[PDB]
Amino acid sequence: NDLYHEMIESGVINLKDATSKVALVYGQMNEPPGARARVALTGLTVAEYFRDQEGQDVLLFIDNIFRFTQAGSEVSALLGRIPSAVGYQPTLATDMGTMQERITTTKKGSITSVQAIYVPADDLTDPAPATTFAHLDATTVLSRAIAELGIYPAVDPLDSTSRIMDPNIVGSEHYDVARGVQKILQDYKSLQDIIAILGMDELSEEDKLTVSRARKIQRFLSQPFQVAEVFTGHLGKLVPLKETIKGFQQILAGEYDHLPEQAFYMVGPIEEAVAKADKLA
Amino acid sequence: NDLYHEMIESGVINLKDATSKVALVYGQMNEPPGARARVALTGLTVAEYFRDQEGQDVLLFIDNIFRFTQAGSEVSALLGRIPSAVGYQPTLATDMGTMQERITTTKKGSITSVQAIYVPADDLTDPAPATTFAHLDATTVLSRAIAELGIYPAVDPLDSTSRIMDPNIVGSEHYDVARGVQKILQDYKSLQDIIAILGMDELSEEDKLTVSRARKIQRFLSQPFQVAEVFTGHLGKLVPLKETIKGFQQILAGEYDHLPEQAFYMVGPIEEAVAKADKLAEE
Amino acid sequence: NDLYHEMIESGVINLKDATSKVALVYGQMNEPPGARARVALTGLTVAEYFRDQEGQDVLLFIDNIFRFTQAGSEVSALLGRIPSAVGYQPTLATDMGTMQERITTTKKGSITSVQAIYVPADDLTDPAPATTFAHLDATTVLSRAIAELGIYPAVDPLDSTSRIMDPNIVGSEHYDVARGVQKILQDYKSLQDIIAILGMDELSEEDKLTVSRARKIQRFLSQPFQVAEVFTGHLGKLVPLKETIKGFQQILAGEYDHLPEQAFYMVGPIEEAVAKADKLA
Amino acid sequence: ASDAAPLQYLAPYSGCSMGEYFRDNGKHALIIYDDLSKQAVAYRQMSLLLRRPPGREAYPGDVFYLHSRLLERAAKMNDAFGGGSLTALPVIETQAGDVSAYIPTNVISITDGQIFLETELFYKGIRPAINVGLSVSR
Amino acid sequence: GVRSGAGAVRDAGGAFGKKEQADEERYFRARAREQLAALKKHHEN
Amino acid sequence: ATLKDITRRLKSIKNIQKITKSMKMVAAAKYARAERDLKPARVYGIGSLALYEKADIKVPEDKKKHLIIGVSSDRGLCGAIHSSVAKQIKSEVANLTAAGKEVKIVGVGDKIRGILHRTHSDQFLVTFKEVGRKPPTFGDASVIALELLNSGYEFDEGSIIFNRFRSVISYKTEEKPIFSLDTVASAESMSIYDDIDADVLRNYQEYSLANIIYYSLKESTTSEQSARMTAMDNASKNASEMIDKLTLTFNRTRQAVITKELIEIISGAAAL
C-alpha cells in the first residue's frame, strides 16, 4: 500500500490518463502458499510481454523471491514428496531455475531485474539462498553484524560480488580502487582477532595504519538514503561513480589519515566528509 | 596399474616364470557398490588359503578397507534398511567384524595384515574408522597437520598405538625412549599455547631447551621413502631398530643440542643427521 | 534406599506411629519408561489429595524433572512419533504443562513443588531445561564452593533467584533488605578479588567495613537444622520470616559490627547471635 | 538450470563419452565438469522423486558411485590402445569453505589432486586464489 | 560440560596459531644460524 | 561455521584465557615486588636529584651534542608504556634537532631499539637488552653508565626519559635533564659549594648519572609490571567474553546437528 501511494504521489502511476510507467503484481504473506508460489510468475509474465512483444527496456523488482521457494516447500509436503535437506522440496533447484531463467535479457529486449532474497536464520548456506547465487550477475549480501555497527546500508564489502567487476568493463582505475579497498578490508578482518583478544597497542605501526584506514573505509561505505530520510533525519545523498571512486582512492592513498573515523559516517561525497571533520574541530 | 608395473619391474611379480610372490585382487571405485563390498572378502580368502592349506606366513595389504563399509552403506538404503547414524547401515559393526575376524593369525598359520583405513573429513570419531580401532593391534594415525608441516610420513606420534609397546616385550630401553619422546612432544604441545601469547623470546631458558628438543624429535621422526623418491628426491632410507633407539635416546639426552633442527629433517640414522649438520656448516 | 533410611533416621518418616510426614513414590531406573513417565503424576495425585480433601499446603518433590522429560521422550519414541528438536517428544511442552499446572494454589489449599533439575550438556537453552524454566517461580542452587566455605545450607545467595522477589509481593521492606544483602555480597566479591590481587591495606575503611558486614551476613545465612541435630549435636532453628528480615536489616545498618565474625555462624535468630557473642570472651 | 534434472544428471556422462572418443583414438582430450555439485543435486532430485530412500543430506546412497564411475573414466591409455588420454577437471562448490562436506569429501577422495581456491586469498589480491599450501598433485 | 585440552591454539588454525608458528620459526632460524656459525668455527679447528 | 570449527576456536580461546590470567597473576606478583623495592629507590633518586633541585643548574645556551636516554624493557604486552616513551623520545629528538643540535639516543630496552630503528637507526649510540626479565639493580645501571661514558660521545647536554610510577593504573612518562658535562655542572651555585675543584665534581656528576639511571630503571620496571598486569587482565576479560559468546554458538550448533541427523534418520525410515 505504501509503494502504491508513493508511486501515485510521484506520478509514476497516474489514475487519470494512460501515462503510468510501472505495473504492480501483489501476492502477499496473507495469501495461501499456492498463491505465493505463482505471483512471481505473474510479474515475470508481465515483464516478459513488455520485453518481447514491445522491445522495451524493463526493470523487474521482486520482493521477496525466497517466499516462492518457501511456498513450494509448503506445498510439496502435501504433494507427497520425500523432503530434501532442511525439509525443502526435492524439486528445489528445478523450479527455481525454471522461474529464474525466464528473467533474462534476450535479443528482443532487456530485463534489468533486482530481486530481494530472504536468508532464513541469517544462514547463507541454507539451500534456498544458496542455489540462487548461480542465477545472479551482481550479488549484494547484507549482514546483520554490519547493521549492528550502524553502517547502513549493511552491504558486506567482502561478500558482495559482481560479474562486470573487471578492468576491461569497469575501467582500470575503478577495478584497482575496488581491489585495494577489498584487500585492506580483508587485512583488517584478519587482524580483528588479535585486536579483539590482545588489544590495539600490540600491533605494528603499519598494522595500526591499515586498521585506521580500513575503519575509515567502513564508515565511508555507509550512505544516507532518500527513502530513509524519514527514519534518521539525514538527507539522502546520491553520489556519482567518479566521485566515490575519487573518494575511496584518496582514502586508500592516505590524504585523509588525519581526520577522525566519525568524519566519514553517513556522508556522501568525500567533500562532505572533510566538511564534517572540521565541524568537530 | 602403478603398483602392478612397479611389482613387475621389482621382480615381485614375474610374468615369464612362476616365481611371483604377490597375488592381486582389484575392485576399484568404478565398480558398483556390490563389487566394492566383496573384493576385501576375495583378497582375504586368498590369504586364508595361503594361511590354512599351506603353512606359510601371509601378508595381506588392503587399500582401502573403508570402501567396504562405504559400499555396504551405499547398498543398505536399497536393501530396505532404516539408516543408522551418519547414514551408515545398521549392520555396520556386524559385517565389519565378520570380515575382520577372518583376518587373524591362527595356529595353522599367521597373516600379517596391513590395512589402510580412509578417515572421512579427517574425523576419527566417524563410525567407520572408529569401529576399526578395536579390530587392530597396532594402529598408525596419519594426521594432516603433521603432513602440512612437511614431516613425511605424517604419522601422529601422540595418536599411534601398538599392543606390543610394553617393557616386557620390546625391552625397557625401547619403552623408555618411546615414552620419553611422547612425553616431551606432549609438553611441547602444552608450551605452544604459552608461546602463542607470551612469545618464544619471553620463555624461560629451561623450556626453550625442551621446545628445541621437541622440534629436533619432530624433524627426526621424518624419513624419506624409496617409494617417495619421485616426489622428494631424497634417497630412500631404512633405519634399523637399534639405530632409531640410539638416535632418539641421544636427542633426548641433549647430545645434539648444538646442531640445527634442519639437520634432523629427512635423514636416516643419527650419523646421517650429524653429516648433514656438518655439510650445512661447510657452506 | 539411602534416602529412605536417611529420612527414617531424621524422623520425618516414622515406622512406629503415624507421625510420618513424607509419602514416597519411587520410580526406579530399571522400570520401563512408561512407569517413570507417570511416577510424577502418582506423587502429584498423592499431593492433590492433601490439597483438596484436607486443605493443606503440600510440598511435592520431583528428583528430578529432567528424568521425567527423558521418560516422556522415550515413551513418545516407542509409539513411533517423529521427534522434535534435540530428539525430544513433540508433546514436550504439552506434557510438561499437564504435569505442572496441577501444581498450583486452589481455594482449598496449595501444592508447592521443589523439583531438582539436571541441565544436559550444561546448556540452559536445551528444550528440557527451557521448558522446565518456563514453569519455575524460583531457583535455589547449592554451590560446592559455599559448602567448602563451611556454610550450611549451601544455598548460593547470589545465583539463587525468585520471581516473587518484587516489592508488590513481599513488601517494600523485604525487597529492600534482600537487595541490600545481595549488593553487599557482590561488593564483597569485588573486594575479595582486589584482596587476591592487591593487599588488604589498599582498600579504604569503607571497603573494610563492607567486607566485615558481608562476612557477618554470609555467616548468618548458615543455619542449624533439626534434621541434623542427631549428627552435629546442634539444636535446629525454625527462624520466622520477620526475625530473618529484622536480623539482616540490623546487620546491614551496622548495629552488630562490633560483634565478632563467628558470633553469627550456625545460629537462628539474631538474639542467639548476640548470645553466642556474649559466650565468646 | 531450466533443463530437467535428468538432463543435468546425464550431462557429465555425455561429455565423458565425447572425451572417451578422443581417448580411444590416439588423441588427447580435456573435460571440465562445472560443476559436479549441481549434478549431485539433480541426481538427488531424480532419486527422491523416484521414491528411493534418502541418505546423508537427503542425497542418495550412491552419490559417491555417481562421480566415481565418471571420474574413473579419465585415463591415460598406453601405446597398445592408441596412446590417448582424457584429463578431467571437476569443479566442486563448497558452502563457506566447508571442505569437509559430503560431496566435496567424496570428490576429493576420488580425484588425484585438489586446487583449493580460498576467498580470503582472493580478496587479499592473490588472484588466482590458489592456496598452494593445501593444493596438491598426486 | 564442554572442556578444552593442551595445544588447542594451533589446532584451531586461527590468527594465534599462525602467529605462534611464525614466532617459533623466526626464533629457531636465528638459533640455527648461530649453531651453524659455531659449528663452522669448531670445524675450522 | 561447522561444529568442529566452533569447538576448535572455543578451545583455543579457552587456552588463551587461561594463559592470560596466569600472566596477570605473575605480573601482579612482580608488581608487588617492584612496589616494595621502589621506596628505597625513590628515596635514593630524590636524594641524587636534590642537589640539582636546590641549585639553578640550567643549560646556558645551544649545545652541539645531546644524548637522550630512553629507559624501557625488552618484554611486550605492556600496553602503551613503550609506545608512550617512544612518542616522547621522538618528540624530544625532533624538537632538539630543529635547533640544529646533534642528537644521539641510547635505549636500554630492545623494544625501544625496534621501534626507533625504522627511522632513528643512526642516532642509536649504544643499545642494551635483557631489561625487565629480572628486577633491575644498581649493577646494571652502573654498567650502562660506564659504557655510556666509554661510548666516546661527549654530550654537552643530556636528558633521560622514563615512565614514572604514579599508581597501579596511572603512570607518567617523565623527562629529567642530565648535566653530565663537567662545565655545565659548574655554575653560580657551585661558588657557594666548597671543594668543588674539577675532578671531584666530574666524578660526582658521573655517579649522579648512574643514580638517575638506576632510579629511572626502578620507576620503569614498576610501571611496566603494573601495565602488564592491567593489560593481561583486560585480555582475560575479552577472552572470557568471547568464550561465552562462542559457548552459546556452540550449543546452538550442537542442537542443530542433533536435530538435522535425527531428521535425516526419520526421513529415511519413513521413505522406506
Image (cartoon, coloured by chain):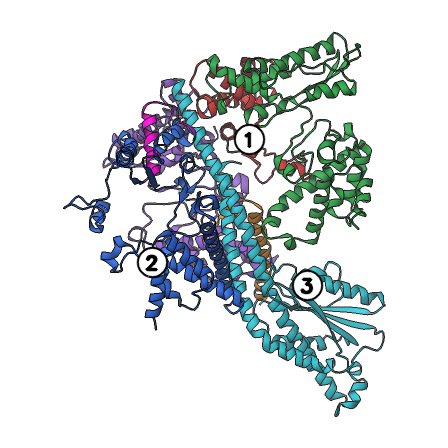
Chain colours: A green, B purple, C blue, D red, E orange, F cyan
Q: Position of residue F125 (x, y in %)?
A: 73, 69
Disc 1 element: helix
Q: Residue furthest bottom?
A: F195
The amino acid marked with disc number 3 is Ile
Would you say C35 lies left or right of A180 here?
left
Frontmost residue, A231 versus A24 = A231
**Disc 3 crowd, CA 10 A, few/some/many (<14, 14-19, 20+):** many
In this orientation, does residue F242 appear? yes
Along the horizontal axis of the image, is B11 left or right of D5?
A: left
Within the magenta stretch, is there residue C169?
A: no
Q: Residue furthest left?
A: C16
Tell me, yes or no, whether the two marked residues, 1 and 3, touch with CB atoms within 8 Å.
Answer: no
Q: Chain of mark 3?
A: F
Discs 1 and 3 lie in a common subunit: no
Amino acid at pointer 2: Gly
Q: What residue is pinned by disc 3?
A: F112
Q: Is residue F130 left or right of residue F269?
A: right
Residue range in magenta is C64-84
Asked whether A40 or B124 is in front, the reply is: A40
Q: Give the distance between the C-alpha atoms of the residues marked 1 and 3, in whole angstroms.
A: 50 Å
Camera-nearest residue between C170 and F20: C170
Query: Looking at the image, which residue is at 56% across and 61% down?
Result: F229
- Disc 1 target residue: A121
How far apart are the two marked residues, 1 and 2, measured between alpha carbons? 54 Å
By secondary structure, the bulk of the magenta-drawn segment is best described as helix
Q: Mark 1 or mark 2: which is in front?
A: 2
Report the mark closest to the observer, 1 or 3: 1
Q: Is residue F102 above or below residue D60?
A: below
